[PDB]
Image 1 (cartoon, rainbow, N blue to C red):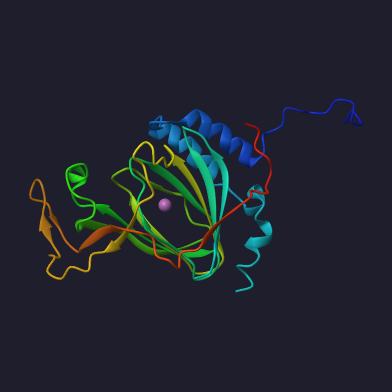
Image 2 (image 1 turned 120 degrees about the vertical axis):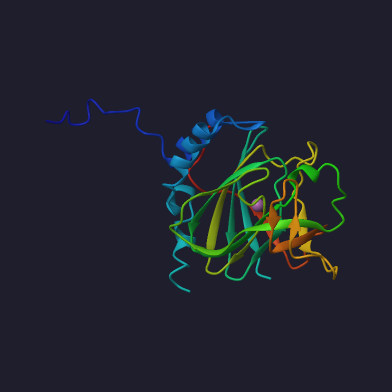
Length: 241
Ligand code: NI
C-alpha cells in the first residue's frame, strides 16, 4: 500500500501565502486587476486565509482574551500590487483616507472592527476641483465586521474608495492593492476630515437628476496626530518571489 518513503508524492499544493502571491502576480498589473474574473481568482484564495498562514496565530488568540499603536506588516510591494497587514489593538483607528485610481481587496483575518466608507458624489469632478475645499461624498458602508466575514472590494470610484477603520477587538486587516500607492504616479494615501463649514446641504441633485441624500462633506487634511503606526517585519511563511 505504501512505498515506505521511497516514492514521495512531491510537487505539493503551495502553502496559502505562496498560492496567493502567485495568483496576484498573474491577476494584477500596474493598471489594476486584469479582469473581474482574474480578481475573483485572487478573492477565492484570500477567503480561505487563516491566522497561521501569515504567522499571526498567537495574536488571534488575543481576541478570546478580550491612541494604541498599530503594526503594519508589508509582505510585498512591486509596480503591479502590494500586500500588507494592519494589526490593530482594541480602540485603534485608521483615519479616513482614499485609494486614488486603485482597487483594494481586503479580508479581516481575525477579530472585529468597524468600517465607515464613502465615495464621491461626483467622481468626474475629481480632476477639476480643488481637493482642499469641501466636496460632497455619499455613505457606502457603516457597520461592524466580525471574523469570519467575506472579503471586501473597493474600486477607484465605487465600493467605498474613502474609508476608515476602528478596532473593536484585536484584529488584523489583510490588504491587496493594485496598483500600489505611489506618490510619484499621483496615487497618494490622502486623509480626509468632515468639513466644519456650516451651511453645506444634506442633499444635492447631480448630473442626471439623481438626488443624493445624506451627503457628507469631506476636506483633505493631514492625518490626526494620535494615529501611531509602526512598520514591523513579516514573520510568517516565506514567499518565493
Ligand atoms: Ni485603506
